[PDB]
Image (tube, rainbow over all chains, first blue to last red; front, side, top):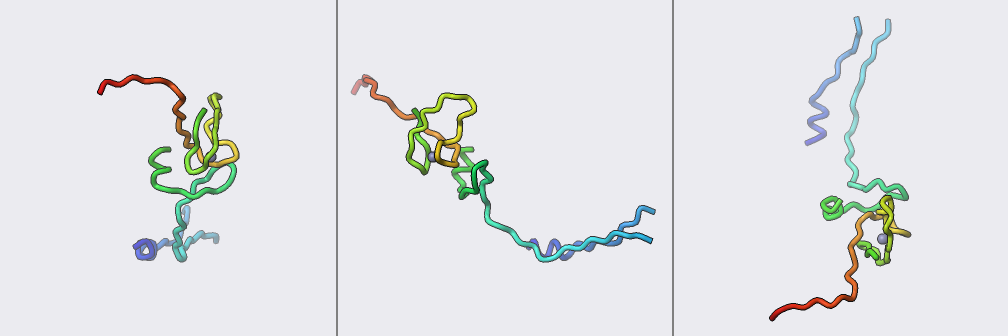
Length: 52
Length: 42
Ligand SMILES: [Zn+2]
């Protein structure tokens, strides 16, 4: 689903009014949820999110 | 005296900023039940 959504959107050239800026999007990757603790990364669980 | 979650360790922390378990990384603590007499009617 996400790959089709990102592939469908096409970014055209950006011109304020020579130099021009164009952007593009590659493969979309999603990582597993992880809690960003102060000490180190920890496993994230649904009940941890519910309690916190 | 407070009990941590997945890790077994007594917190015993009463400071306001102390919410994270010592020698641990999780911030979930359970209050421990002391030895107190409670009367119930059957
Ligand atoms: Zn702990």
